[PDB]
Length: 185
Ligand SMILES: C[C@@H](O)c1cnn(C2CCCC2)c1
Image (cartoon, rainbow, N blue to C red; front, side, top):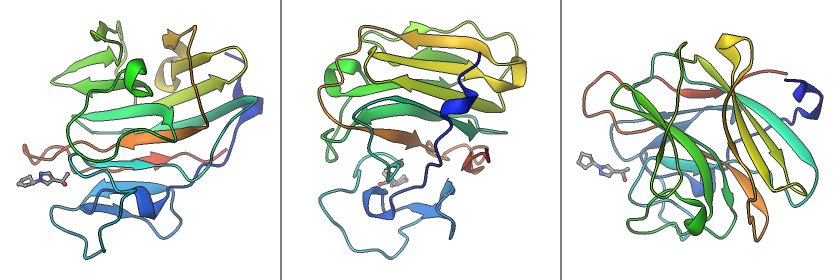
C-alpha cells in the first residue's frame, strides 16, 4: 500500500485507560499491570476490559498509524466513536461504534456482527491502520508481510469524531504481558 504519507503521531489518553493499565511516560506504549494502578475512577475509563483510547480525534481526512503486537496472545485494535460506551459489557461491532480486528486463541477476526474470519499466512508483529473519514473506510495491513491487506471495513457510518482504540487483552495465561507499542514514523 501507499498510505504511509498520511502518518499521524498517536499518543494514549491516560484518562480513558482502564485502571489496571500502565501507559509509558512518552504515552506511546501500554501494558496490562496485573493489579490496580492507584488512579482515581472517572466516567471516561473503560471499566470491564483492559482498553484505552488515543488522545487524537479525527473528523476529516486520511490518517495512518502502526502498532507493534510482538509476542502477544490476545489484543483488539482499530478506531471507535468518541461516544462509545465505557462502563459495563459490550461487543466490538460497528453498531456499537467500533471498527476493529483482534487476535484470540491463535485466530484473527474482524469485529463485524457476527465476527468475520481473517486469512493471515504470516502472523503479524506490526499492524498498519488506515482511516479515510470521507470515504467511510477503515483498513488493516500486515507490516510483517510487506504491507499485505488484512481487512477493509467499507460503507462505515462513523456518526461522530473517531479515536484510535486499543485493547491489550487479559493475561490469565501469563503469556500475554507484552505491551502494545505505537511504532515510529
Ligand atoms: C480489566 C480490569 O478492570 C479487570 C477486570 N477483571 N479483572 C481481574 C479480577 C480478577 C482477575 C481479573 C481485572
